Amino acid sequence: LLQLKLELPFDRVVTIGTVLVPILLVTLVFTKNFAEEPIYCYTPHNFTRDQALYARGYCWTELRDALPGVDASLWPSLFEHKFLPYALLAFAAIMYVPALGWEFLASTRLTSELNFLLQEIDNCYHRAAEGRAPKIEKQIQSKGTEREKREIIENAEKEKSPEQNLFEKYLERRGRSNFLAKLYLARHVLILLLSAVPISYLCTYYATQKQNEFTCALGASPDPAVRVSCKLPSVQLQRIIAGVDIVLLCVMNLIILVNLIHLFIFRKSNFIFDKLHKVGIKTRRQWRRSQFCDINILAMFCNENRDHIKSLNRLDFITNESDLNVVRQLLAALAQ
Amino acid sequence: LLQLKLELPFDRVVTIGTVLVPILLVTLVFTKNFAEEPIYCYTPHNFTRDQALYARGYCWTELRDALPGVDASLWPSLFEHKFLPYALLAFAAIMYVPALGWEFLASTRLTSELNFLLQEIDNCYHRAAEGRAPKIEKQIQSKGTEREKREIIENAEKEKSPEQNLFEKYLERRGRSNFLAKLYLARHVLILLLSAVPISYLCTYYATQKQNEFTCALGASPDPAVRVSCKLPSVQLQRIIAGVDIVLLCVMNLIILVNLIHLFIFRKSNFIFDKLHKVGIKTRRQWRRSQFCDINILAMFCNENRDHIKSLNRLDFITNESDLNVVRQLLAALAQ
Amino acid sequence: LLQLKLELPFDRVVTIGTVLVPILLVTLVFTKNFAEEPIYCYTPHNFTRDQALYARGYCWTELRDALPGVDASLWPSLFEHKFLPYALLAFAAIMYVPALGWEFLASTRLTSELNFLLQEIDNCYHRAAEGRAPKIEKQIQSKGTEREKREIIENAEKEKSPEQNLFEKYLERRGRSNFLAKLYLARHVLILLLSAVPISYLCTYYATQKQNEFTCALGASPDPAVRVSCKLPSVQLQRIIAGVDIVLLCVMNLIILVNLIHLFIFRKSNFIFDKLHKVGIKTRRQWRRSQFCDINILAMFCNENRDHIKSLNRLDFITNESDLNVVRQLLAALAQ
Amino acid sequence: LLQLKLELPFDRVVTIGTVLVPILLVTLVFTKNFAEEPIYCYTPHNFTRDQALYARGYCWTELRDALPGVDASLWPSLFEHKFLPYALLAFAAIMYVPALGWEFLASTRLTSELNFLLQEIDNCYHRAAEGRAPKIEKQIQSKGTEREKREIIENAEKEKSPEQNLFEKYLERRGRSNFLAKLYLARHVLILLLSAVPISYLCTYYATQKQNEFTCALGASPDPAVRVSCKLPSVQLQRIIAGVDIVLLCVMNLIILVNLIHLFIFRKSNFIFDKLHKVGIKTRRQWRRSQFCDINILAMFCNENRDHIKSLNRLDFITNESDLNVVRQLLAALAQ
Amino acid sequence: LLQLKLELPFDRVVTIGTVLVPILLVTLVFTKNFAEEPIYCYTPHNFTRDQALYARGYCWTELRDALPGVDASLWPSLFEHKFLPYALLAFAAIMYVPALGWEFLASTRLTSELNFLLQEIDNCYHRAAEGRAPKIEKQIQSKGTEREKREIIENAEKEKSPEQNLFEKYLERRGRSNFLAKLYLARHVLILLLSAVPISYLCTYYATQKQNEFTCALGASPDPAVRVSCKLPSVQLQRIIAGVDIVLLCVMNLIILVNLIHLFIFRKSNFIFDKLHKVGIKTRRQWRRSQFCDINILAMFCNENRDHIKSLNRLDFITNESDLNVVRQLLAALAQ
Amino acid sequence: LLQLKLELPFDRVVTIGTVLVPILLVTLVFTKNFAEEPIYCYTPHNFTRDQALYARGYCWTELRDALPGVDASLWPSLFEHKFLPYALLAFAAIMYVPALGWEFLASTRLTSELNFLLQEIDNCYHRAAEGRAPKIEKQIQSKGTEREKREIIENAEKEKSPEQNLFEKYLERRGRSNFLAKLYLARHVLILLLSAVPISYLCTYYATQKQNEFTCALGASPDPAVRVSCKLPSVQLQRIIAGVDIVLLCVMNLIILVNLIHLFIFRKSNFIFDKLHKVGIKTRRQWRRSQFCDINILAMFCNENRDHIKSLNRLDFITNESDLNVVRQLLAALAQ
């Protein structure tokens, strides 16, 4: 069985909104184009049924307008309409280097450091019935105010208990090694820069390629040049999925930006040492100086895994329901 | 094994009736249109078999009527008939934001708070054979009316028993935090508003797009303009699934409305604290002031899970069969 | 269950970057060519619909230009355009001899020598609670500086302990048998040489095969020779995937080169005896003379397997957090 | 679970190099031929579109040149070009009698005699901690040179120990019954002779069938004979996979030859009694007279299975690291 | 798990050689015929493109030559060429009654009588360490030639031991009930007779149906009879798989014959009571009178299962290695 | 695991012989007809290529001969040839009511009464080592002819033993309730009557529908009636699978008849109380009066399950080998 997942809901949403519907919007064009004649041309009268097939298969691989008067070098081309069944397929696979920079680069160290937290660090507040319940509040009832609780509670974590080498040493080591925040940031700030020529390419295409009717010109008749006006069927649908992707990809560059700015400059609630700060383990103000620690990133992964761990669920029901007396009934409930 | 499901029958019915038969009613149109010629046109006599293909493939990508006398700008268009193979496919995928606002936003906290109720809170009335059976009614038989039962029964839950920190504290905490009701309501009131332009779009289409016969006009003959009257095959079937969806989607904006109004203004039977109110745990009148608590929502999820939990099945057989003496034989049955 | 994998991320990246998208870029050409007419020719007027099929199916299996004036031996050929649907398929299968030189040649000895390390050598620093904890620092606390720790710590590994025949003998045996480094190097230096005629073939093709219009010539009319100018559709797309592969394969010959040079001449951090050099087992300077030992290669495989081994994860949390006192609390934590 | 495999890497390489790429090189021809017109013929002018179909489907089932002047009996045929889509398919299935001479003839006796070695003969040198460790070197330490070790070590295997009826009796029985070597040799020397008419058939085809243009002749017009020159499309590709197979099958007749000659005349290291000859069980020179024993074949199968047997892996780490003192620390390590 | 198989290698070879490649040689004809025009006819000049389709689809369902001069009753037919795509399919399913006469008639009794031998009769020579080892040779060592071993060994099986009701009673019962030999013989002697009209049918077809060119005649022109010479494409390939099957089926009637004759008249080594005749259980000469017992058939099934039974594998290693002293070390090896 | 099967081999043979090859003989006709032109007609000369398509698609949906002279009401029809692609498909599904009268009507009671026999009634003659072995023959050896064995053996089953309420009460209850024989007979006598109009339909079709050439007549020319003689391709193959089914279904009405008559009037060996009649449980002559009991039907189901029940296999080896002293060695073998 497995309970630890390395993907946030934000990452899944980004993946399904910038890599997936790309692909699902491309097969429509492929199935529309392959189910129709590539081009329609107005062949002259005295053209046999096989002599007019050359005129229809020759102006499709050429795609060159023939403006009267001008030379043969200033003829505008139309290769873009033919070329981007695939240009939409080369942009849905480029958006994988950021996605593959996690499953192949940091898919072992992070889960190695997290499975330890899963299996080892679980004795807090689920084994406290015999660990600390008959210790702190057992002597408080049998005495005799409000200026003595701190004195007794101080000699719980500060004392070099056997269950202390696994706590406050991780905080001291990972409280300055900002390595994970130097890679998860590169996971999102890179996808914000890769989504640039995606947008910059099919933005001038939407504004400079509109026409779908050109006068193709053949030559070298077998014994005079003949000109036929042709027509391109699938131009009206190509630039309907060529500017829906514009807003679909330009709106994913805003939610990522706001997420990244609010995580690194506004939000200061880890839940990895804030939820467990009132219940006995108080952290000295050595973290407020910088929010770039890896513990902030580990906090999200810990938050995403709260269900399959039964001890943490017991803690959630037994800790946060009285957040602000409470210890009066705890001693009478666990006095076994 | 799994026994807790997070989907109500109402949600499943809504999903299969507003997202599914949408899709199953679209493939019919796709398979009907792709199995026939897109358009039929009445070409003139002196037209070769390849010169008349341009006239049949050019008036299908144009779709513009040619009324006599008027200019070239006041010609009505017919792109709607061509366009909504897909407009019916863009409305069956829009109906997922309300559906994906539950599996990705509140698919962890709710089941985290419910699996605790599944595993932890089960000692009530299945362990009562040794928990309360030799306590309350054991002394009632050996005495000596109707003005003393309450006095004895009061010192069962009011007393700070060891099995009391898990009860009446959840009621006190979740009795004012109306968070779940602020999201489940947003899951249904949003699908009632998303189903608006679905209906407002293909309602004017049913009333303004009727004709299927237009006189297309070509031009620029290779050496006079020629006009051909054409015909659209699949117009009589498109607007048969374009107004069956009207009633199919306008009838799901009424059952959701009546469900939401009757849950929030009429129904006041939780079954999460009403069924268990006569059997010993009596709740003070602190809930009647508001029906917006999360416990009301948890009541539906608890109701949907009554079978795979054998203890609750024992309770159902052993509690509700004598709802209104009864305790006379209970002491004689469990006196082991 | 299995936890040891014999493939590095570098090998997987190389395989998916030089063997895979090769294949994925070939099916596009096959599906493009098979969905169009192979060639278009300008047949004369007095040609029946079956007499012009010979002219279209005869200049496609010939593919020979007919320059006027010259003889029948100096006619340039065009077989390259027809021939390399498949020449791109014979280069995606040649890149398997290096890939199959590992799964069939050294896929048993390496994992045989590694499963021993997995199952056998695990008692270090996870069984040390009863193995060395009450031995070294137990007597240090109960005495009486900085010139005596080495004297006590010397008689731990130097002494012929029962758990010593499995250590420092592997180092002595594999410290001079440079066999694995004589094969893993041949695994990569061979793929750097196999990727030569791949590049040298479709490099002159990109520079000497440009034209796609030739004047084919028939003969032996059934009672004069007739010449028809033909046209090749799929030439403009063939040399778009014939020079994207150039850079796609010429860029994989640089990362492999830098990896191989920096492994064998710049990196001197094994992590197989460097991480475990401060924590008690100190290695004499018998390795610094050569970096060609098999232990360097085994170090990478050990690094790739750090998660599923729980003892090594415990070591990682309990060893490297205080790398540079520390032993003061270790005795008080494991004094059971 | 299964750990014993009956196929050597050499056999797998031979199978995938002489039976498989045969097959993958045939489907290409089938998909190329079936995707094109079988033949192209130059029909005369006054031929209707259905009268010229007989001329195109009649010269394809005839395939007979018509040289002028000669009679109707000296006309060369061209049936080979039509015939060997399938002649390449009848040679990829003939190469199975040697392959099916092992899975049906000796796929039970060999693995029956090998599972005994797997399960029963495993007590050597893994149970020696209590079997021979306190026996041989336990008395060597407690005495008092180099002329007494043999005397003590002699009375270990020579003595009729309880674990002796399973050793040196197999050597005596299988040391003269050369049955397996009379069948494995027939498994390879037969595939060297079956790969003869494969090569001898499509070697004269590569040298005598070159032309692909013949003048077919019809007759019996319905009221004079008419001759039409035809053309065969797929002749230039058929003899490209008709001489790549020549070298592909003529190079597999050399590696098999060198393997067979070096196994039977040069290599004399079994590893089935050579590796285990220094560690206590010394074999008398009764094997050097002939290398045709079945133990030589069993040696390869034992070598291919060294990983899933953990006892043999322990032996490999604990035996060969000191091959050439060593026993000085073995007594101190296993003195439990 | 299952270890007993009811199919001999001979039966599998027969099934794959007379039922399988039949089928694999039929799909080739079906895919060849369905990928070509059924017939080619030389229609006259003044025939429209739809009037000549009747002449091509009418002489294919008629298949009747028209010899000049003779009447309309002496016209040879050609229905055999059309009829035996399927006549080759009705002979590959007839060869199943002998194959289905075993899985439905004797697929329960045989394996019922064999699973008993598998599970019950296994105590011989694997439990002999405590069953007979301290009994026969234990007293031979402690005495005091060659005229006394038989006297002691006689009172081992002749005596009415507890493990005797399961031995020599099966021999007495099944030593005269020749029922299985009356059915397995019918399983092979029937397939030798069913494969007769298979051969007798397509033997006259190979000798009397050669021509593939007939002059079909139409009639009743809508206002004179017109004759057209037609041609059959697939006649030269039909009789290439119509005489390869001749030898393929006539060679399977010889190996079966030699197997059956040598089993019933030459071979007299059961291995079911011959291998176990020297090791203590000696059978009286009551079997040499007839080799038609069912024990001979059970011997083959026992031989095919010698691997998954580890006790019999131990016996095979420990019994046949000294077949012709030997008992001298057996007592010293099993004296526990 | 499951060992009890409710289908006899006779039922499986019937199902595969009257329901299966029906279906397998229908797809051949469907694939033959759909791969050819439905009809061929001899259109006149002055008919355009689209005016002759009406004549070919109009005489196929009419199928009415036009005899000269007679009126328009006495024209014979030919709808049968078109109609029985499907009439052969409506007869392969009718043969399921007898097949579905067992899996839905008596697929619970029978296996309910048989699983009891499987699990409960197994103590006979496998537990007899301690149940009856030291009881009957233990006192016979220690005494002192042939006129006393019956006296001792009588007080074994006649006595009201604890293992007697499960025996001879089933015989008394099911010895007169002939319910199962009233349904299994209806399962076969119904399939003998359902296979009637199957045969009676395609028997007159084989004798009255022979011709496949009719002169169709059109009319109402757009400004005289025109008659065209047409031809039906697939008539010669339809009545080849229309009279092979005749004998294939008329031969299944004989084996069922002989089976039913011999079961109910000739065979009088149940094996459910005949095999177990000599070994101690003797049945009084209360069954010979009628063979219509359900125990006779249960006997076949018991016979089909003799393998997976190991106790019954032990009984088969230990009971029937001495059917006709025998008890002399049984006491000495089981005297534990």
Image (spheres, coloured by chain):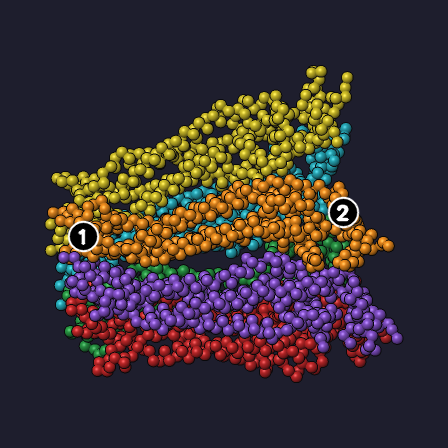
Chain colours: A cyan, B yellow, C green, D red, E purple, F orange
Residue B112 lies, in percent from the top left, at: 57, 38
Which image quadrant is residue F41 in? bottom left
- Measured as percent of width and height from the top left, residue B150 is found at 68, 19
Tell whether D219 sits left or right of B127.
left
The residue carrying mark 1 is F227
* Res C281 → quadrant: bottom right
* Residue D190 or residue E227, whichever sits in front: E227
Q: In the current view of this chain or complex, which residue is farthest to the right?
A: E144
Q: Is residue A240 above or below residue F331?
A: above
Pick whichever of labels 2 and 1 is earlier in the sequence. 2
Left or right relative to E197: residue A278: right
Does the image show residue D35? no
F203 and A196: which is toward the camera = F203
The amino acid on which the numbered mark 1 sits, given as a three-letter code, is Arg
The N terminus of chain D sits in image quarter: bottom right
Q: Which residue is mark 2?
A: F154
Q: Residue at x 62, y 26 (%)?
A: B321
Residue E51 left/right relative to A12: left
Say which quarter of the image contains residue F307.
bottom right
Residue B331's spot in the image, x, y percent?
72, 26
What element does badge 1 sit on?
A: strand
- Which chain letter goes with mark 1? F
